[PDB]
Structure formats: C-alpha cells, structure tokens
Amino acid sequence: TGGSVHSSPAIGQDGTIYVGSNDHYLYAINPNGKLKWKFETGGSVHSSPAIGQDGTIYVGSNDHYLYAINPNGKLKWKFE
Amino acid sequence: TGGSVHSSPAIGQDGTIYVGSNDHYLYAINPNGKLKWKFETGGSVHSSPAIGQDGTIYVGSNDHYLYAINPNGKLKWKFE
Amino acid sequence: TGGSVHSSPAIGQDGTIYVGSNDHYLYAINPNGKLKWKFETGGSVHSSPAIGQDGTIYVGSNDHYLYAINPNGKLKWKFE
Amino acid sequence: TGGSVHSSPAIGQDGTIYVGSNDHYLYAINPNGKLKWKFETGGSVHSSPAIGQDGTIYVGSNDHYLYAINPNGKLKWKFE
Ligand SMILES: [Zn+2]
Ligand SMILES: [Zn+2]
Ligand SMILES: [Zn+2]
Ligand SMILES: [Zn+2]
Ligand SMILES: [Zn+2]
Ligand SMILES: [Zn+2]
Ligand SMILES: [Zn+2]
Ligand SMILES: [Zn+2]
Image (cartoon, rainbow over all chains, first blue to last red; front, side, top):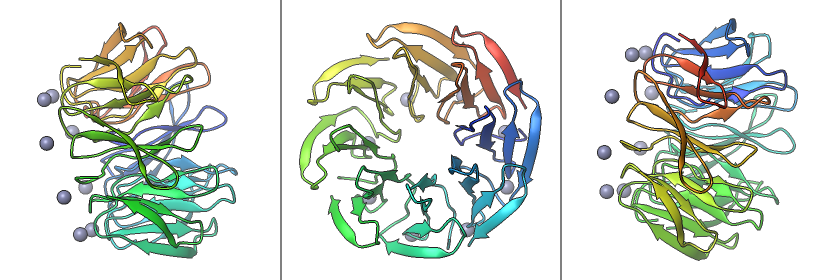
C-alpha cells in the first residue's frame, strides 16, 4: 500500500484479500497479488475488515466512521 | 461514531454489525446502516468484540473492564 | 482486569472467554462472569488470544514471547 | 521472538501457529513450540495473519506491504 498496514487481512469466499492501510484506503487484492479495487476514506484504516453473509465488507476508520462497502468497491453506507 | 473506530467489527447471526469506538461506546448497527443500540462504557473501546453461542457480546475497555452485553443492549456483567 | 483491556476476547468451546490485559495477565472467565484463572506474563498483553483444536490458548506478550497455555492455566511452552 | 509480539496468532489446519513480531519477522511455530520457519520483512509486523483456503499466509507490515507467504516460508508476492 502507501503506508503502514497495521490492520489485519480478511479473506472472502472467492479468495480476495481485504486490508486497510495507513494511506487512508481499504484494499481488495486478488490471490495472484494484483489490485482488484481500492476504496478511499478520510483517515487511516487501523481496524480490521469483516465480511458479512452477502459479502459486504465492514471496516472502521480514523475519520469516526464505520464503512459498509459492496464487493465491487462502491460505498453501501457509512455510519458516523 | 463520535471518534476514531480503531476496533474491528464483529457480525452476529442476523447480520448485526458490532464495533467499539473511541467515544467510549459499543455500537450495534443493522445491515441497512441504522443504529440498533449503543452501550456506554468508561473509556475508549479499542478492542474488538466477540460473540458467544447465545449471542452475548464481549469486548474490553480502557476503563480496565471486560464487558458482557446482552443482544438487546443491556449489561450482562463486567469483570474488573 | 487491573488495566486497559486493549486485546480482543476469544471464546472456547464450553463458553469460556479469554482476553489479555495491560496488567500483564491473560484472563479466563466463565460465561457467568466469575474468574476461572489468570496467567501472569512479563509485560502487557496487547495481542488477542487464539484457541487451537485441543483447546490450547496462544497469545503474544510485550516481553517478547508467544505463550502457549493449557486450558487449566498452566504454561505449556513459551517461544522467545 | 526478538521483540514485542503485538500481533495476534493465527492457526493453520495442521496446528501451526503464525504470529508477527516487532523484530520484523513473521513466525511459524509447531504445536510443540519449536520453530518451523521465520520470514524477514522490512519493519515491525503489528498486524495479524490470515490463512487462505490453500494455506497461504497473509499479513501486513510497517514497511507499507501486504505479504503473501507460502506454507513453506517462501515469499509468494507482496503488494506495495
Ligand atoms: Zn511509512
Ligand atoms: Zn493521514
Ligand atoms: Zn477524531
Ligand atoms: Zn476518552
Ligand atoms: Zn488504566
Ligand atoms: Zn507494565
Ligand atoms: Zn522489548
Ligand atoms: Zn524496527
């Protein structure tokens, strides 16, 4: 990523690895190591992502938000 | 939330997302992004929640406590 | 506990909650909230415990060690 | 290890414990407590490892990288 990866990776059902970074982004990476997508938040993502039963990704941010992100990298919602 | 969300979200059997915040609270949020309940502790909740077999939520706090909280947001117990 | 509980609780097959504390200890607590045992390490336990298939508890410490602890609270081993 | 173990251990299907350390290394340890292998990264490993369906280990580092490491301790890839 573009900064320290303090957060811990989660794995989806098709093998995708999700992890947050200090550069403010949540990363989605393919098992072959090429970027799937990146989602841009307002602060460092120290917390670790969780995957719901439909494949929604949830992760917290230093900008005071819990994000919900669809498997395709579009925002679902963010609770402040 | 009202501060940095350093802690990592847990997911219940009915889809509820649980996460602690720096504003001292444990949050319970519905998959549609509306607040279910919030439980108020004495310090920042950096640690990540765990869900037991009956659905009790456990999480630690900076106020020296491990909290046990019923699925409805009432305190079960807190060990100091 | 006796200090900030930064670490995140793990749950055993019989419901026991395990969490580390800043007071240097790994705690084992019963679902009713009474202390089962406490194991004493050389520094703050920020990391979160894992449970193996036989029920061994593993957790790291600030004293440079990964601890392995039997379900009864006796040390199995510690790798430095 | 050679420094604080802030990160939280993951367990493989054959019982191996994986944990990162502050001495910059990801450790693979056998249930009997003897070192299996150690993988050397460019900074402190605060984040916690995840295990994929083929047994690949993923963990982040302070050197800005997410590492993918084969079960035998050779690098698979690292995304920067
Ligand atoms: Zn850096
Ligand atoms: Zn920043
Ligand atoms: Zn803030
Ligand atoms: Zn405060
Ligand atoms: Zn204190
Ligand atoms: Zn101390
Ligand atoms: Zn040290
Ligand atoms: Zn260093």
